[PDB]
Image (cartoon, rainbow over all chains, first blue to last red):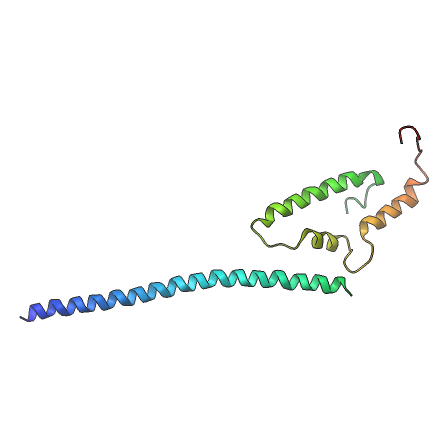
Length: 60
Length: 78
């Protein structure tokens, strides 16, 4: 009866929504990790730029 | 600068303070990426762009103006 099909459809929608929220959570986590390692790379680059400034000032 | 406003006998207090600063740099380096202590020290001593630094310049100034004309040597105690 229509109620049975209704239960089936609601279960379908529930599965799809769960998948969508999994995708969103992955997006958030990936963004956080990328921020962290970008900060690290930037710091490393900054440490290197200052060092080359100092060296080339010492050699001239 | 605190060395530069004192006699020659304060070189010991100077290197003591420099060692304290080096230990501080070593401790803070565990978490932060700072310039090497040598680079910082040379920048502070004006010894990057020039041959001699402030410490040696003040050592010579002190020699000339206060050490040669004011001190008495003792051979036995050295």
